[PDB]
Each structure stands twice: as C-alpha cells, then as structure tokens.
Length: 217
Length: 222
Image (tube, rainbow over the protein chains, first blue to last red):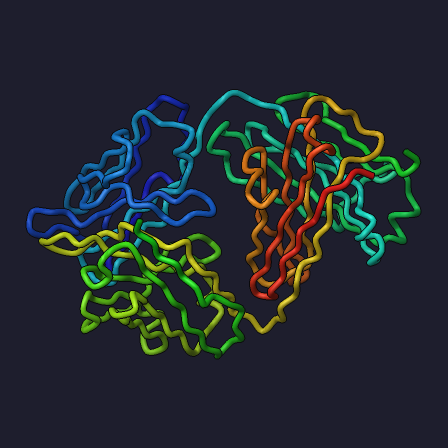
C-alpha cells in the first residue's frame, strides 16, 4: 500500500508570492509514461476539489496560477501567484495501485499585516435564564496574527471554569482569524455578581482590550 | 450541471448498520467509475471503496472489507454504500466521488458530493437550545453592529446555521463546534451596518437533522 508524505505540513506565504509543496511516494506511481498523482484543494466546510490530475494536467475551471510537476516518486504543486482565496489544505493522491491513498495534507496560510480584533460581548438571553443557565459570549473578530489570549473576570476576579473557546480557519477574503469565547454558569451564580468582562490580549497592542457587561446597566 | 447528492447519514449505535445513497444527475452515470471516500474528524482523507462503470468489479480498503458493501443501480443513477458492524473508527463525513473517464489508466476524482455525516456512538441524540445574542443595553452604536447566535447542548454534529435564510452571507463567522461533557456547542456572529438593525430583521436559522430540529430565532434588542 503506497504511502504519501507531504512537505511541509504547513506553509505561510504573502499575497502575490510563490508557494510550492511536495509529495513523496513510497514507491513509483508511473505507468505508460503517465504519472498517476493528483492534487486536491479542500477549503473548510467544502468538499475537495480536483486541481491537477496525472501530475501535469490542469483540470478545466481552475486558474492557471496552479501547476504541477514531477515523476516517479517525487511531485510538486506550485501556486504562483498566491491569492487570498487559496487558503486551504492541499492533498496529493495516487491512483496507480489500489488502494488509492492520500497524503496527510499541507496547510496553506497567508501572511499579511497585523490587525487588532473587534471585540463584542453579549449578556445572557432571558430565554436561557428561564432554563437555569447563563452564558456570556465574547466574539473577537478579524485579527491577525492567529495567536491570542482571552481572560474572563467576574467583579474583578478571574474565572477558568465553564469557559469554552473556538477558532475559525483563516478567512478567504481578508485573511484574518476570528474567535469566540463562552462563559457558562448557573442563573443562581450569574445573579450574585454584577460585572462580567472579557479581556483579550494580542500582539497588536501592549494593552489588553477589555469589553464589559454590567448587570446594573 | 453535474450533481452528486449524498444522503442517509445519521447517528448509529456501535455494531449497527446504515445505508448511504448518492443520487447522480447531469451526466451519464454508467460511463464513470465511482468511489466513496471518508473524512475523519482529524481531517485525514481515506478512500473506502470503488465500483466500476458496470458494477461488475468492486474493491475495498482494508479497514472496511467484509463489513461494507458498495453497489450501483445504473437505471436509477444511484450509488450505495451498505455499512454493517459499525465502530467508532467509522465516524466521518462520507463523500461520493465520480472518477474522470479518461483512457490509458486509473483516474482522479473530478467531482464530489457535499458529503453526508455519520456518527457512531452509544450516546443519545439531543436537540440544540438556540439563544439570541443581542448587544447589552449600555453599548455604543459606531457604524457596524454585531449580533449572534449560540447553539448549545446538542448531539451529534452537525448543525447548520444561516442568517436571514441565506440573504446575509458576508460578515458572518460560524465557529466550529466544541465538545464538553459529551454535548456540542457552537456560535455564530454576524456583522451588519447600524442603520439596518433593528429597522430590518435579523434571524438565525438553525437546523439539526439528527433530531429533526429547525429553529428560527429573531434577534431583538433589549
């Protein structure tokens, strides 16, 4: 069973520049002069899309900035020039010998200028309160780069329990990232305190960005 | 237009069975090899099974051999995957793929369905609770305003979220689901200009096939 190893595992490139990614096969994928190595693009929440078939050939409907070369056990995909819409995971596949098998994929990320997050905080909905729960939600949208820290505080005091975080993949329009952070407590405990605050800390700024919600109004 | 529409995906208990379907249209079904391919939650792609144009020849990956059976009805433009003896390994998104019809050897998969989700678990289906997220009463209106929607306490994945039934597509972030105490939670935000809300109406639409749930939550100020 043929094994495909892709390099690198991730790659970061600026808009307009060149990106190349490799695939090594454990044995040859050649036959009849043709090479049976294909490349696919998968964007988040979408199925894989065929880009290049048989090592060289561009699938119809695909921009000419994509190209492939190689033979035998060594193959490359080139993207030049890179665009915002090319954020994706790329996979190589061989069809020479059943079973067909896939490389572990290569993540293409874009470099761009630093951007500070827009932060929004949301109190509990009253429909949630009726059921005995209380979540406070904080969105931190459209920042670069990806690394970021979020801290919750109740009446000055930090909380780490009942906090759930989630991060988007890089955006394909503006190349930014986003995050949400949720804090869940009981209605009972929620009603005992007044001040709920999310504090974001990010490369963009030496000071933390604070958004706050007060039950006094 | 070429289409492949998978269906049949559901929550199944371990040792259980399931049949997936792919309805093809817009091209000659019987001139093309077909495959099933799955994507596991760590995002590896794994080819599962293939079937020849005629349906005479089939081949299967080692992990599914003797448990899964691929078949086609060329009269109905339908591809099938019969799964039995299901394990946790088998939890994935299953895609139906069409092979290219080129001569001189084996082919790439030039078209893929959107995929159908299959979860193998002893746990019970739970419908989501959906909560509106409207800005706090003391907050400041500065051109743009962000609203959102919290979808909490459901099983299994997936849920689908849209805003104004699709009319709102940009300035939307829908965050991947996160599991806690064996229940998923996600959220979605949407950003619009301050004039448009609360004048016009903003509603999140949430669907959870596995519990036959569909909720439309209007975002109202406080």
